[PDB]
Image (spheres, coloured by chain):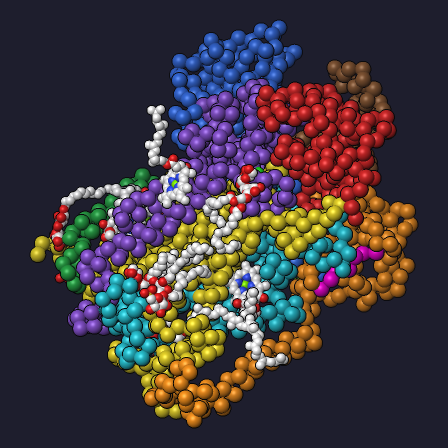
Chain colours: A yellow, B purple, C orange, D red, E brown, F green, G cyan, H blue
């Protein structure tokens, strides 16, 4: 056909080693830009005045960091939610000072990962698959939106978005506990249930299927040689697996339907991680974890502490120390 | 359904930001102060207090070297200092009387602050939209006493959750609708498996 | 060398005791109590409302035994230095140069021995479980019986789980 | 320990006269203090001016002395700065500025006594924690 | 040798009494009648060569002067310490509760 | 900075245009079954 | 949890980090495997609900490994091809994770922490303009210790007068 | 005229007002009237830093720097009495205003120079017998430069002057003396020097405008290192009033 119809045929081709697709056409450049900026900044960027108090924090390896302490540092609190592209700055010198690379990385990354999700829908359509893998991916993606975009929005600043580094991430967690008591938030609790459960059922499923592989290999060769790519027969015996698990707990506590079993494997961590994302996205608007501080009172009115109150004492330590030069007035309101 | 789900998710998200930032169609008199507004009210409250005490608020240098009460935005406008620097885009009827062409006006700050402005700023500072899920108002380390969560937090949080699940609903139904229109929503035909008819990748 | 035992006193001549660092703490404040545990002096963080600083309380320190025996120090920075050492208990002079020492505590052989052995003991538990399992299940290491009767894994077909002769 | 008649006995006036509150007034005082005051004075501190707290010793050194029912009742009618030099009804809630502090509109004299009673009783229960702020949480 | 000037000041009368030349204004709340009106005036008109000089502040009512007189035993004066007086720190020194 | 801005605007418009026209070009038909 | 952060700086510890990788990687493997099976199912029934189109005793795979493999290869660049490997890997990742966290906790029994990076401390001690996220988090820890210890460790009878408590400006 | 919403985000809020090319007049001074500057505005256009050579036989030059803190540099709303002296000179005595801005500039090679750009406590004078302020009038004066960080500021390990630790707590047993400079915070107070060269006058309005150059020390990080010498140049504007 015409040049365009050939292009369309290529973009959407089921035969490319890596699927491109229309989402891919946005995904490829945005992810490349984010990746490249990230790598260069992580290695070489100068210190960033994250809290807009002229107190530049060093993130990069060349400026005295290791893999663990290193980061791409959030953009200046003096910027807030203003859009700070490279052309808004008088120079790259200024751009680097104010944390411009962070906005560039997280914006291209979020667009790219959103397209990564669209691309998963797309390929499954091209391949005649059912379409919901992309929905499972919406859970980590939502979590990434929570810490890089929604939280900044609620709090009025990208300086409060998660830093793009290991120790930075911990800083974000700790300040978050001080300001929102995230541990006492039931959406975070559902998140824990989601990831602890996800790990558990992973270990379980892995182990139940493995324990049930049909004898196909010699006593010396890997059992993996007992399964061939594309074979039509199922490589393990699900009835034996159920016979084991149904007896481990009780019969009806166990799955004999592979389809409902794999559904539960998809649903449990995905829903729990949705709640995690929504925990962060709703504490973005300062609806916080349960507060039982001084909840138990004695007959006279003496406060009888609980474990909630010892949590409070730790949160207070975080609160008063964090960003030790940034507050001038008595309440931290964002 | 899926198209409508997508448009509702989008609208939910817009609604979340509307109630969070906007104080015209969500008047702070009824809905409580915005987060930015309450943060701006705190700096105004202490500026008032301290200047009453004799402080020259324009030339008071804070620990970092930036002005304790007043400083410049990145484009030069006079704005409140401390953390609330981020909130300098806030505009509110108790505050605009002090704003001149260059931002907050030091002449007006020194002479023209009316009692009703002090009152509203104290009110808004102390009704910031922060509180716990069990409706203890305050920071997360606050003791029980005040039963408050701003209507703004309830409206933003609820609608972020709703907009979010609607987006999922959109992906679910869009993807299911595509598959059902093409005829493979119930699974792969074992005897016409598309991948088996394609060249191998490598 | 031992520097000798530091005794601290306020301007009243009352003996003061530095609260010792518990092991849990990487860093620890300097607080001096009287013999009944009442706070008498400290090293403040915020100074503007300080009430118990060494300067205000006239804290001095005298040494008995060791290198500094019979000496008394009244310069506040000096007294404050000895008190920071006193959170570690008895005060010693060290050579920090021969080894380019960094001033940060390390454990001893007792600590290193304990760590390696508790870790190796725990990992040896997995080793036990693994080999025990290989021992008792040798017959199924390459997989289960390719035609294991569905009756032995389904329910109520046998009286005793696994026993073919307990058929109903 | 109990909320006893001794705990509930507080100075009525500057001249050493006491008054014993009932448990019901105490509870009333706590309720109405929450209703009208705690947004700024939760815990005996003052959010909008932390230099001034509701500690008994602080109240005693106000002018006029506010460490008694009568002093507190009068504060709630016609609040002053700490040196009594200035009338701050325009920026501090009181019966005098119930037009602009609308929660003040249905506080009766008896309500004012109950709140004063709360303010004087709490530190007798909580000690330094009353007016102590976060250090004491 | 280098010295922390604030710690040093705690060794002088600034560590014992309200120093009219240095002490942050919230300290005046500790005595009847000083805060906010006299405290504002004392800080605005500092430094003082002696404690008594506080009585020579222009515009004082008679009871104002009398309150000053009653509280002189609680005051002191030392040299202006730059670190205590810069940054408007006499008005707000960054300490709340 | 201005040329940078203009270059990027052009870049982004190009890719956005590809994405829009791309899905406008009979996407539902691009599947292996019913077309 | 918070005690471990403040006192042991447990987040810095590489054995806890492998733990996190195993737990989050396990949860990822769980979500991704369950979703992949469910979206490469064969049509073995007429029902628009597909759960009934499975038989525990049936010989055949209920989903296409072939399509699943092609999908991930083109999406992510790599895919499983061996189902026995895939499942073994699902056992391996979270199990190994939890084992690693255990080793770190054995370390913490002895206060043998991964608390500090000495090179950062020396630079920071000598250069008061040097700051990283690692220095920032230690100030948080020192806040946690000072503020929680007196009520959390009552047998120590800690009395920390207000003036000694570490605090930043205002707060 | 222009309102806040005309100006917001343009850069104009950091710009001192200018005078027309017709503003070449003379503003008469009556030695019997008292005056004030009701608004002094200083907009920097160049920051120069004096290089520090390895041998002090080389002549050290002021070199250009790049501004990295954006349009947050101008001093404004400054006011104070304008005295007429015995000899007819004028003296400006600054009483108040937005009279400092923390500024960071970068040397070639990337060294960052923080400074507290300021005219705090400015006392500036003209030449004698100033019967009118003209485009030939100049002010020359001195001002104070207090520490760039005020006394509560805590370094990254928590150490400070009026607050903070007094030691390097991460090195519990290191020797103190080598770290004394880092551990014992100090608060500088130095002098700076400024010159204001009038170039425009509206006699009908009391407004003047011209160029200025000042010199002051940069941040010494609370005693931790030696400050550099900075030279700031820009435009100014002032409104004089009978008062
Ligand atoms: C564990 C349980 C097991 C889980 C499995 C069961 C399925 C889940 C259902 C949860 C069960 C909840 C029990 C309901 C009790 C309750 O809620 O009780 C609370 C109230 C009723 O109690 C009253 O609650 C009030 C709530 O405060 C409110 O009222 C105050 C006084 O006027 C203040 O104005 C304050 O500002 C305002 O917040 C006060 O505290 C009153 O004293 C008290 O009597 O129920 C209400 O309000 C009714 C409101 C329900 C609508 C919810 C709206 C949610 C919007 C946000 C969505 C996103 C947020 C997600 C985060 C999670
Ligand atoms: C797919 C390609 C792509 C996309 C989507 C982006 C996107 C972005 N770039 Mg990146 N970039 C790319 C490729 C891309 N870049 C490449 C190849 C390079 C190297 C040359 C760069 C180098 C670069 C730099 C140096 C910077 C960016 C920045 C940005 C951001 C702002 C761009 C902007 O203002 O557009 C404005 C242009 C438009 C709005 C044009 C759209 C006009 C159409 C006709 C209207 C339709 C739009 C509509 C709202 C929605 C689309 C349809 C929808 C319904 C599906 C944004 C995250 C900046 C940033 O990160 O700041 C923090 C920044 O500084 N880019
Ligand atoms: C639990 C379910 C639930 C509940 C209880 C609410 C409740 C609410 N929503 Mg949410 N919503 C939900 C689910 C829900 N929503 C979901 C799933 C979505 C999509 C994600 C949304 C999206 C949404 C948006 C986008 C908005 C709300 C808003 C609101 C609030 C106002 C509703 C309103 O006025 O509608 C409008 C009512 C109608 C369209 C019905 C017709 C109304 C007529 C035209 C009004 C006539 C008025 C006029 C003056 C009369 C003239 C007469 C004259 C001649 C005298 C209310 C608190 C608003 C808000 O407060 O957000 C912060 C808002 O902007 N909701
Ligand atoms: C996370 C965002 C996201 C994703 C991955 C999808 C995915 C999908 N959509 Mg939905 N959509 C969304 C949000 C999304 N949607 C929203 C918020 C709306 C409300 C307007 C819609 C409205 C919609 C309609 C009306 C249709 C779909 C359809 C589809 C499906 C087919 C592909 C398609 O036509 O895409 C179209 C994609 C969009 C309309 C939005 C994609 C947004 C992402 C973020 C990419 C944007 C890239 C952009 C060029 C970058 C801007 C850069 C900027 C700086 C200029 C596919 C499952 C089609 C389908 O088959 O329905 C059953 C269809 O007809 N969608
Ligand atoms: C991304 C965030 C994240 C993630 C994924 C993890 C993940 C993990 N953490 Mg870390 N944590 C984090 C952040 C995180 N942490 C942060 C920021 C901190 C602050 C420093 C901590 C502080 C922390 C501590 C202090 C500890 C962990 C531990 C762990 C491990 C716990 C494993 C487990 O399931 O134990 C759950 C418990 C078990 C699995 C034991 C067996 C339980 C039996 C089977 C229970 C049977 C129940 C029975 C049926 C009854 C039910 C009754 C019902 C009524 C309740 C795991 C690697 C632990 C660890 O490392 O262990 C070695 C640990 O002690 N974490
Ligand atoms: C001293 C004396 C007196 C001694 C006498 C002793 C004696 C004789 C006692 C007998 C008397 C007696 C019974 C007393 C009772 C005492 C008592 C009640 C003890 C119980 C205490 C207790 C809490 C026990 C256990 C609780 C328990 C097991 C909780 C588990 C709940 C739970 C999460 C269940 C799982 C539910 C679920 C949906 C699981 C599926 C998820 C999963 C594992 C997926 C992986 C998976 C599953 C499959 O399904 C198949 C197929 C495959 C492939 C696969 O991947
Ligand atoms: C107190 C007042 C009460 C009112 C309030 C109620 C509100 C709550 C609403 C919730 C109802 C949801 C019902 C959905 C059932 C369903 O999934 O059907 C789909 C399949 C079909 O089941 C399968 O059913 C099949 C038959 S069929 O498909 O249904 O026809 C069969 O073949 C198969 O063996 C069988 O397992 O369900 C299953 O596979 C069984 C196990 C999984 C079901 C629960 C998990 C789903 C989400 C996980 C939970 C996440 C939360 C944890 C967070 C960390
Ligand atoms: C700083 C930023 C620098 C950016 C780097 C630029 C990278 C450019 C890479 C070009 C690849 C895009 C062209 C592929 C497009 C392509 O190669 O198409 C191949 C296509 C093959 O046709 P068929 O549809 O028959 O193939 C299936 O022919 C065309 O339609 C044209
Ligand atoms: C929220 C909804 C949870 C389900 C979404 C999981 C996503 C995992 C990734 C895709 C995994 C995937 O591909 O799944 C596919 C799986 C089976 O597909 P089928 O095509 O057979 O059925 C779905 C449609 O085709 C309609 O028949 O879908 C379901 O089982 C839907 C169950 C809906 C149950 C009713 C609505 C939602 C309630 C679920 C229970 C939650 C309880 C709340 C507790 C707090
Ligand atoms: C748009 C494209 C997006 C591109 C993303 C690029 C993704 C790179 C993919 C991983 C490639 C490495 C695989 C080597 C290993 C390799 O070649 O595996 C290929 C292997 C193939 O599995 P089979 O089932 O074919 O193997 C047969 C077995 O029986 C072996 O005997 O896949 C797996 O084992 C899956 C589980 C590991 C998946 C691990 C992913 C790890 C993520 C990386 C984490 C560290 C990152 C460090 C950051 C500095
Ligand atoms: C900023 C957004 C831009 C706004 C534009 C949106 C307005 C709508 C304009 C629609 C007009 C174009 O209409 C659409 O375009 C492309 C390119 O011409 C066509 O062309 C395509 O046809 C078939 C469709 O099966 C494809 O297989 C083929 O590869 C391609 O050539 C579409 O079949 C046509 O339906
Ligand atoms: O910046 Mn980051 O952190 Ca959210 O809170 Mn406010 O602001 Mn800042 O202090 Mn707390
Ligand atoms: Ca050495
Ligand atoms: Ca001239
Ligand atoms: Cl921090
Ligand atoms: Cl602040
Ligand atoms: Fe499986």
Question: Which image quadrant for residue C167?
Answer: bottom left
Q: Which residues are magenta?
A: C17-23
The secondary structure that dominates the magenta segment is loop
Q: Residue furthest bottom?
A: C165
In the rendered image, residue C13, in percent from the top left (x then y), is placed at 91, 50
Image height of A95 relative to A174, above or below: above
Left of A233 or right of it: where is H10?
A: right
Is residue C20 one of those drawn in magenta?
yes
Q: Taking the image as four quarters, which one is ligand 5 found in? A: bottom right
At a point 53% along the width and 14% down the height, the residue shown is H240
Left of G89 or right of it: where is B130?
A: right
At a point 58% along the width and 22% down the height, the residue shown is D100
In the rendered image, residue C135, in percent from the top left (x then y), is placed at 49, 91
Query: On the rendered image, what quadrant is the N terminus of chain A found in?
Result: bottom left
At a point 31% along the width and 47% down the height, the residue shown is B5
At a point 60% along the width and 25% down the height, the residue shown is D101
In the rendered image, residue G83, in percent from the top left (x then y), is placed at 33, 77
């Amino acid at each position: 056909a015409n040049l365009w119809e050939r292009f369309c045929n290529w973009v959407t081709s089921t035969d490319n080693r890596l699927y491109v697709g229309w989402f891919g056409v946005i995904m490829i450049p945005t992810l490349l830009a984010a990746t490249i900026c990230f790598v260069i900044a992580f290695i070489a960027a100068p210190p960033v005045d994250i809290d807009g108090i002229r107190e530049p924090v060093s993130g990069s390896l060349l400026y005295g960091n290791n893999i663990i302490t290193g980061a791409v540092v959030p953009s200046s609190n003096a910027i807030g939610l203003h859009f700070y592209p490279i052309w808004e700055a008088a120079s790259l010198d200024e751009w680097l000072y104010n944390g411009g690379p962070y906005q560039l990385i997280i914006f291209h990354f979020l667009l790219g990962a959103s397209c990564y999700m669209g691309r998963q829908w797309e390929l499954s359509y091209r391949l005649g698959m059912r379409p919901w893998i992309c929905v499972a991916y919406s859970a980590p993606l939502a979590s990434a939106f929570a810490v890089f975009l929604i939280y900044p929005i609620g709090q009025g600043s990208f300086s409060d978005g998660m830093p793009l580094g290991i120790s930075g991430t911990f800083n974000f967690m700790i300040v978050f506990q001080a300001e929102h008591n995230i541990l006492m938030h039931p959406f975070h609790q559902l998140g824990v249930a989601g990831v602890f459960g996800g790990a558990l059922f992973c270990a379980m499923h892995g182990s139940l299927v493995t324990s049930s592989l049909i004898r196909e290999t010699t006593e010396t060769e890997s059992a993996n040689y007992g399964y061939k790519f594309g074979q039509e027969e199922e490589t393990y015996n699900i009835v034996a697996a159920h016979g084991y698990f149904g007896r481990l707990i009780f019969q009806y506590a166990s799955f004999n339907n592979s389809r409902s079993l794999h559904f539960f494997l998809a649903a449990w961590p995905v829903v729990g991680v949705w709640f995690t994302a929504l925990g962060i996205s709703t504490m973005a608007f300062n609806l916080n974890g349960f507060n039982f501080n001084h909840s138990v009172i004695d007959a006279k009115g003496n406060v009888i502490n609980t474990w909630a109150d010892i949590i409070n004492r730790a949160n207070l330590g975080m609160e008063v120390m964090h960003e030790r030069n940034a507050h001038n007035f008595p309440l931290d309101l964002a | 359904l899926s198209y409508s789900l997508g448009a509702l998710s989008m609208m939910g998200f817009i609604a979340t930001c509307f109630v969070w930032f906007n104080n015209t169609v969500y008047p702070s008199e009824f809905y409580g102060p915005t987060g930015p507004e309450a943060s701006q009210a705190q700096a105004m409250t202490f500026l008032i207090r301290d200047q009453k005490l004799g402080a020259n608020v324009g030339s008071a240098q804070g620990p970092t070297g930036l002005g304790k009460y007043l400083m410049r935005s990145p484009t030069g406008e006079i704005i409140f200092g401390g953390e609330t620097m981020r909130f300098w885009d806030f505009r509110g009827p108790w505050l605009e009387p002090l704003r001149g062409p260059n931002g907050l006006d030091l002449n007006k700050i020194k002479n023209d602050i009316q009692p009703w402005q002090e009152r509203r700023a104290a009110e808004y500072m102390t009704h910031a939209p922060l509180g716990s899920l069990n409706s203890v108002g305050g920071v997360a380390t606050e003791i029980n006493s005040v039963n408050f969560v701003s209507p703004r937090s309830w409206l933003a949080t609820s609608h972020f959750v709703l907009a979010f699940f609607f987006l999922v609903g959109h992906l679910w139904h869009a993807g299911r609708a595509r598959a059902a229109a093409a005829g493979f929503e119930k699974g792969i035909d074992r005897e016409s498996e598309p991948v088996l008819s394609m060249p191998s990748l490598d | 060398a031992w520097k000798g035992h530091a005794v601290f006193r306020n301007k009243e001549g009352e003996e003061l005791f530095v609260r010792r660092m518990p092991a849990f703490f990487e860093s620890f404040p300097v607080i001096l109590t009287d013999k009944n545990g009442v706070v008498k002096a400290d090293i403040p963080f915020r100074r503007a409302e300080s009430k118990y600083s060494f300067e205000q309380q006239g804290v001095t320190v005298s040494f008995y035994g060791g290198e500094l025996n019979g000496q008394t120090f009244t310069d506040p920075p000096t007294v404050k230095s000895y008190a920071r050492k006193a959170i570690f208990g008895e005060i010693f002079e060290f050579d920090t140069e021969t080894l380019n020492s960094d001033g940060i505590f390390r454990t001893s052989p007792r600590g290193w021995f304990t760590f390696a052995h508790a870790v190796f003991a725990l990992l040896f538990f997995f080793g036990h479980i693994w080999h025990g399992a290989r021992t008792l299940f040798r017959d199924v290491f390459s997989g289960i019986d390719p035609e294991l009767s569905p009756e032995q894994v389904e329910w109520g077909f046998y009286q005793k789980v696994g026993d073919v002769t307990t058929r109903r | 320990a109990e909320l006893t008649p001794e705990v509930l006995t507080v100075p009525l006036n500057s001249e050493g006269k006491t008054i014993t509150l009932t448990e019901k007034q105490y509870l009333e005082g706590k309720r109405l203090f929450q209703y009208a005051c705690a947004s700024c004075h939760v815990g005996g501190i003052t959010k909008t001016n932390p230099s001034l707290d509701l500690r008994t010793e602080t109240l005693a050194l106000a002018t006029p002395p506010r460490d008694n029912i009568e002093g507190l009742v009068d504060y709630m009618k016609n609040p002053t700065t700490y040196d009594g030099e200035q009338e701050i009804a325009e920026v501090h809630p009181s019966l005098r500025s119930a037009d602009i502090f609308p929660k003040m509109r249905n506080l009766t004299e008896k309500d004012l006594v109950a709140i004063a009673g709360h303010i004087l009783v709490e530190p007798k229960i909580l000690g330094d924690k009353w007016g102590g702020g976060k250090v004491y949480y | 040798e280098l010295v922390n000037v604030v710690d040093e000041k705690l060794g002088t009368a600034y560590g014992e009494k309200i120093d009219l030349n240095n002490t942050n204004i919230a300290a005046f709340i500790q005595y009847r009648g000083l805060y906010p009106t006299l405290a504002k005036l004392i800080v605005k008109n500092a430094p003082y060569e002696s404690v008594e000089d506080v009585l020579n502040i222009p515009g004082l009512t008679e009871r104002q002067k009398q309150i000053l007189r009653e509280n002189l035993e609680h005051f002191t004066v030392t040299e202006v310490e730059t670190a205590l007086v810069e940054g408007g720190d006499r008005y707000n020194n960054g300490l709340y509760k | 900075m201005e040329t940078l801005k203009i270059t990027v605007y052009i870049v982004v418009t190009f890719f956005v245009l590809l994405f829009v026209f791309g899905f406008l070009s009979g996407d539902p038909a691009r599947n292996p079954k019913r077309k | 949890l918070l005690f471990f952060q403040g006192f042991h700086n447990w987040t810095l510890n590489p054995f806890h980090m492998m733990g996190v990788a195993g737990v989050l990687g396990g949860a990822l493997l769980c979500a991704i495997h369950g979703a992949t099976v469910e979206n490469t199912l064969f049509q073995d029934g007429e029902g628009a609900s597909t759960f009934r189109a499975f038989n525990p005793t049936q010989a055949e795979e209920t989903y296409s490994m072939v399509t699943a493999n092609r999908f991930w290869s083109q999406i992510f660049g790599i895919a499983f091809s061996n189902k026995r490997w895939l499942h073994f890997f699902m056992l391996f990742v979270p199990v190994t994770g939890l084992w690693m966290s255990a080793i770190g906790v054995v370390g913490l029994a002895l206060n043998l922490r991964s608390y500090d990076f000495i090179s950062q401390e020396i630079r920071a001690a000598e250069d008061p303009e040097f700051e990283t996220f690692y220095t920032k988090n230690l100030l948080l820890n020192e806040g946690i210790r000072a503020w929680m210890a007196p009520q959390d460790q009552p047998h120590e009878n800690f009395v920390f007068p207000e003036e000694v408590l570490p605090r930043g400006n205002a707060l | 005229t222009l309102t806040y919403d005309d100006i917001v985000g343009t850069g104009l809020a950091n710009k001192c007002p200018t005078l027309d090319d017709t503003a070449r007049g003379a503003y008469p001074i009556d030695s019997s009237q008292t005056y004030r500057i009701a608004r002094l505005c200083l907009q920097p256009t160049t920051f120069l830093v004096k290089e520090e050579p390895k041998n002090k036989r080389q002549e050290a030059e002021f070199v250009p720097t790049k501004l990295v803190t954006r349009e947050t540099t101008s001093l404004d709303q400054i006011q104070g009495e304008l005295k007429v002296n015995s000899d007819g000179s004028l003296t400006f005595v600054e009483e108040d205003g937005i009279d400092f801005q923390p500024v960071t500039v970068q040397m070639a090679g990337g060294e960052r120079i923080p400074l507290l750009f300021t005219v705090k406590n400015l006392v500036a004078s003209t030449q004698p017998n100033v019967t009118s302020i003209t485009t030939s009038t100049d002010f020359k004066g001195e001002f104070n430069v207090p520490s760039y960080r005020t006394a509560n500021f805590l370094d990254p390990k928590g150490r400070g002057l009026a607050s903070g630790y007094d030691s390097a707590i991460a090195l519990p047993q290191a020797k103190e003396e080598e770290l004394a400079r880092a551990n014992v915070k100090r608060f500088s107070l130095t002098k700076g020097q400024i010159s204001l060269n009038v170039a425009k006058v509206d006699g009908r309005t009391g407004e003047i405008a011209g160029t200025f150059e000042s010199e002051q020390l940069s941040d010494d990080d609370m005693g931790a290192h030696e400050p550099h010498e900075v030279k700031i140049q820009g435009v100014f504007y002032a409104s004089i009033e009978p008062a």
